[PDB]
Image (spheres, coloured by chain):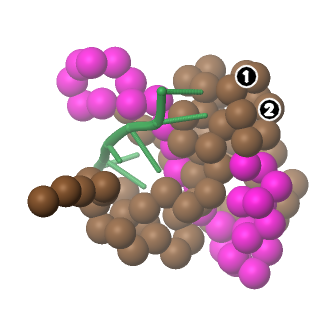
RNA sequence: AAGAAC
Protein backbone atom coordinates (compact mmCIF):
# COMPACT_ATOMS: atom_id res chain seq x y z
CA UNK A 1 0.00 0.00 0.00
CA UNK A 2 0.96 3.68 -0.34
CA UNK A 3 -0.27 7.17 0.66
CA UNK A 4 0.05 10.86 -0.28
CA UNK A 5 -2.10 12.76 2.27
CA UNK A 6 -2.64 13.29 6.01
CA UNK A 7 -6.24 14.60 6.15
CA UNK A 8 -9.57 14.87 4.28
CA UNK A 9 -8.78 15.29 0.52
CA UNK A 10 -11.81 17.60 0.04
CA UNK A 11 -10.57 21.22 -0.38
CA UNK A 12 -12.79 23.84 -2.06
CA UNK A 13 -12.00 27.27 -0.50
CA UNK A 14 -8.85 26.65 1.59
CA UNK A 15 -6.26 28.68 -0.26
CA UNK A 16 -3.01 29.25 1.64
CA UNK A 17 0.65 30.22 1.87
CA UNK A 18 2.45 26.95 2.48
CA UNK A 19 6.10 27.40 3.50
CA UNK A 20 5.54 31.20 3.90
CA UNK A 21 9.33 31.60 4.37
CA UNK A 22 8.79 31.48 8.14
CA UNK A 23 9.61 35.23 8.11
CA UNK A 24 6.09 36.53 7.30
CA UNK A 25 2.74 36.51 9.15
CA UNK A 26 -0.99 36.49 8.48
CA UNK A 27 -1.22 40.26 9.09
CA UNK A 28 1.11 40.81 6.12
CA UNK A 29 -0.36 38.06 3.96
CA UNK A 30 -3.90 39.39 4.46
CA UNK A 31 -2.91 42.63 2.73
CA UNK A 32 -1.30 41.21 -0.38
CA UNK A 33 -4.16 38.76 -0.91
CA UNK A 34 -6.74 41.51 -0.33
CA UNK A 35 -5.38 43.07 -3.56
CA UNK A 36 -6.85 40.16 -5.55
CA UNK A 37 -10.24 40.00 -3.77
CA UNK A 38 -12.07 40.09 -0.40
CA UNK A 39 -10.73 37.88 2.42
CA UNK A 40 -12.84 35.71 4.73
CA UNK A 41 -10.10 34.48 7.09
CA UNK A 42 -6.38 33.72 7.41
CA UNK A 43 -4.33 31.29 9.53
CA UNK A 44 -0.73 30.29 10.35
CA UNK A 45 0.01 27.03 12.14
CA UNK A 46 2.89 25.73 14.27
CA UNK A 47 3.42 22.60 16.40
CA UNK A 48 1.80 21.77 19.71
CA UNK A 49 4.97 20.97 21.70
CA UNK A 50 8.40 20.99 20.02
CA UNK A 51 10.34 20.21 16.79
CA UNK A 52 9.89 23.94 16.03
CA UNK A 53 7.15 25.54 13.96
CA UNK A 54 5.46 23.74 11.06
CA UNK A 55 5.84 27.24 9.62
CA UNK A 56 2.92 27.39 7.17
CA UNK A 57 -0.43 29.01 6.57
CA UNK A 58 -3.91 28.91 5.10
CA UNK A 59 -6.15 31.64 3.61
CA UNK A 60 -9.88 31.89 2.93
CA UNK A 61 -12.01 34.04 0.61
CA UNK A 62 -15.67 35.13 0.61
CA UNK A 63 -15.94 34.43 -3.12
CA UNK A 64 -14.00 31.97 -5.29
CA UNK A 65 -15.32 33.56 -8.50
CA UNK A 66 -12.37 35.93 -7.91
CA UNK A 67 -10.13 34.07 -5.42
CA UNK A 68 -9.29 31.74 -8.34
CA UNK A 69 -7.07 34.51 -9.75
CA UNK A 70 -5.53 35.28 -6.34
CA UNK A 71 -4.25 31.68 -6.46
CA UNK A 72 -2.90 31.76 -9.99
CA UNK A 73 -1.20 35.18 -9.59
CA UNK A 74 0.34 34.91 -6.12
CA UNK A 75 1.75 31.40 -6.65
CA UNK A 76 5.57 31.34 -6.56
CA UNK A 77 5.56 35.10 -5.86
CA UNK A 78 8.66 36.65 -4.29
CA UNK A 79 8.47 37.24 -0.53
CA UNK A 80 11.84 36.04 0.76
CA UNK A 81 13.29 34.83 -2.57
CA UNK A 82 11.79 31.37 -1.92
CA UNK A 83 9.05 31.37 -4.60
CA UNK A 84 6.37 30.54 -2.01
CA UNK A 85 3.42 28.15 -2.43
CA UNK A 86 -0.04 29.73 -2.91
CA UNK A 87 -3.20 27.74 -3.74
CA UNK A 88 -5.63 25.22 -2.19
CA UNK A 89 -4.21 23.40 0.86
CA UNK A 90 -6.44 20.36 1.75
CA UNK A 91 -8.62 19.42 4.80
CA UNK A 92 -10.63 22.67 4.22
CA UNK A 93 -10.73 24.18 7.77
CA UNK A 94 -8.89 23.88 11.13
CA UNK A 95 -9.00 20.80 13.39
C1' A B 1 13.49 23.10 2.17
C1' A B 2 8.35 23.34 1.73
C1' G B 3 2.77 20.66 5.02
C1' A B 4 -1.35 20.10 8.66
C1' A B 5 -4.21 22.86 11.92
C1' C B 6 -7.36 25.66 15.72
- In front: A73, or A16? A73
Chain B palette colour? green
Local crowd size for mark 2, using a 10 Å CA cut-off: few (<14), some (14–19), many (≥20): few
Residue A52 on the magenta span? yes
Please say whether residue A72 is one of the residues in the magenta stretch: yes
Q: Position of residue A90 (x, y in %)?
A: 43, 61
How far apart are the alpha carbons under marks 1 and 2?
Answer: 6 Å
Query: In the rendering, at what x and y percent does residue A72 appear?
Result: 76, 60
Q: Which residue is mark 1?
A: A80
The answer to whether mark 1 and mark 2 are in CB contact below 8 A is yes
Q: Is residue A90 left or right of residue A1?
A: right
Question: Element under label 1?
Answer: loop
Q: Residues within 10 Å of mark 1 (few under 14, many from 20)?
A: few
Q: Position of residue A62 (x, y in %)?
A: 67, 73
Position of A60 relative to A55 (above/below): below
Q: Residue A3: where, in percent of width, then height?
A: 23, 56
Residue furthest right as drawn: A35
Q: Chain of mark 1?
A: A
Residue drawn at the location 60% of the way across and 33% of the way down: A20
Q: Is residue A5 visible?
A: yes
Q: Which residues are magenta?
A: A47-75
Q: Residue at x 24, y 19 (%)?
A: A50
Is residue A31 visible in the rendered structure shown here?
Answer: no
Pointer 2: what residue? A78
Of A95 and A85, the residue lying toward us? A85
Q: Quick one: which chain is brown?
A: A
Callout 1 and callout 2 share a chain = yes
Seen at 70% across and 77% down, the residue is: A63
Q: Quadrant of residue A19?
A: top right
The circle drawn on residue A7 is: none
Query: On the rendered image, what quadrant is the C terminus of chain A found in?
Result: bottom left
Amino acid sequence: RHVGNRANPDPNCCLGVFGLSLYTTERDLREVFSKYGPIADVSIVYDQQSRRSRGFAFVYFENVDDAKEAKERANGMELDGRRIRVDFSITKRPH
